Amino acid sequence: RSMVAGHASGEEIHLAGSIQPHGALLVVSEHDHRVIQASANAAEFLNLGSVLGVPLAEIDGDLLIKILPHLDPTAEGMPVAVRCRIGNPSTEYCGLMHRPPEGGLIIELERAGPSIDLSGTLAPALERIRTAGSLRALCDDTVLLFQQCTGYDRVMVYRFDEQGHGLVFSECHVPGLESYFGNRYPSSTVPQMARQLYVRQRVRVLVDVTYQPVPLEPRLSPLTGRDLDMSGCFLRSMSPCHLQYLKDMGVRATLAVSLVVGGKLWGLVVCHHYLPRFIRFELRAICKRLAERIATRITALES
Ligand SMILES: C=CC1=C(C)/C(=C/c2[nH]c(/C=C3N=C(/C=C4\NC(=O)[C@H](C)[C@H]4C=C)C(C)=C\3CCC(=O)O)c(CCC(=O)O)c2C)NC1=O
Ligand SMILES: [Cl-]
Ligand SMILES: [Cl-]
Ligand SMILES: [Cl-]
Ligand SMILES: [Cl-]
């Protein structure tokens, strides 16, 4: 840090090596079911005395009993989310599990909330999507639906053209904010490797733009000797160049949902808040569902 000067002292976004602090991340080796990497906050987040090197079986609570049914790997059910209790004092979490191509089993834990009961909201949302008669109507209904379901201060459909340039194609926002409707932005604002990642990982939640990243410990995977592939991690810390851009805009929190059409990133539903904001698993899942439905309608509309 300060003690190293002289000449030698002078981005792959999926290899962040760190998470956002609203969750905890465990990496488990499946030969022994022991934690081989964890976010540095994990023991305090989960109210455990220790975490790194611990067998899942010995972790206070029921995480192991809750994940066992999903571990047999042929069952091609992952990624999957489980609800469990961990820690002393005990807390309910939702645990999102997936396997990176190498490096073990990742378990990302957020504090659990209640059941969200939006099925009566969702029936008519689905009818508006399925009957929209043009892309203009579809995307205008999309921003309204998402704003209603998520409550973010601004919701946009950010559409990509053939050269990758961004267009704010639809927008809705709370009274008195600035409108970005119809603004165009260069393709460089969403780099190609981000777009590929957003084809894999269809929802991103940035809770607080100002957060301090929480590093994984150890940083390198003990299984691979490389950084952990965090492409599938919903807690992944986001590129600092992006976080600066958001700070420059005065945005505090974001939710983005991919629109994938014919296997390409067609656009994004992009939501901004002016205070920190988190949407829990059950709501993210509904967002994902809506985005699949929208992409189906876009495919039909385009011919
Ligand atoms: C209304 C205006 C608006 C713009 C222009 C905007 C750009 C944008 N950049 C990104 C992502 C990234 N941008 C950049 C890079 C830059 N951006 C710049 O302005 C610089 C020239 C350039 C270096 C700072 C990078 C690396 C990402 C990936 C973020 C990540 O997923 O970690 C996303 C996806 C957000 C998400 O999925 O959470 C969007 C939507 N997001 C917006 O809401
Ligand atoms: Cl393993
Ligand atoms: Cl159309
Ligand atoms: Cl139009
Ligand atoms: Cl404030």
Image (tube, rainbow, N blue to C red):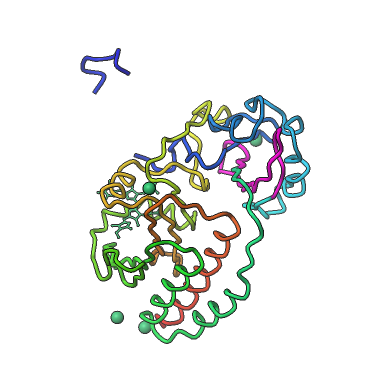
Q: Residue at x 45, y 48 (%)?
A: 207
- Percent across and percent down for residue 158 are 34, 65
Residue 211 image-quadrant placement? top left
- Magenta-span inclusion, residue 90: yes
The quadrant of the picture occupied by the N terminus is top left
- Percent across and percent down for residue 273 are 39, 56
Q: Residue at x 54, y 59 (%)?
A: 284
Residue 5 image-quadrant placement? top left
- Percent across and percent down for residue 119 are 63, 72
- Percent across and percent down for residue 26 are 60, 36
The quadrant of the picture occupied by the C terminus is bottom left
Q: Residue at x 63, y 63 (%)?
A: 116
Residue with the most extreme top position:
3
- Magenta-span inclusion, residue 106: yes
Secondary structure of the magenta portion, mostly? Answer: strand
In the depicted view, which residue is nearer to us: 143 or 240? 143
Horizontally, residue 168 falls left or right of residue 300, namely: left
Horizontally, residue 189 falls left or right of residue 54, namely: left
Horizontally, residue 186 falls left or right of residue 269, namely: left
**Label total for image:** 0
Figure check: 182 above or below 203 = below
Q: Residue at x 58, y 74 (%)?
A: 122
Q: Which range is magenta?
A: 83-107
In the depicted view, which residue is nearer to us: 190 or 243? 243
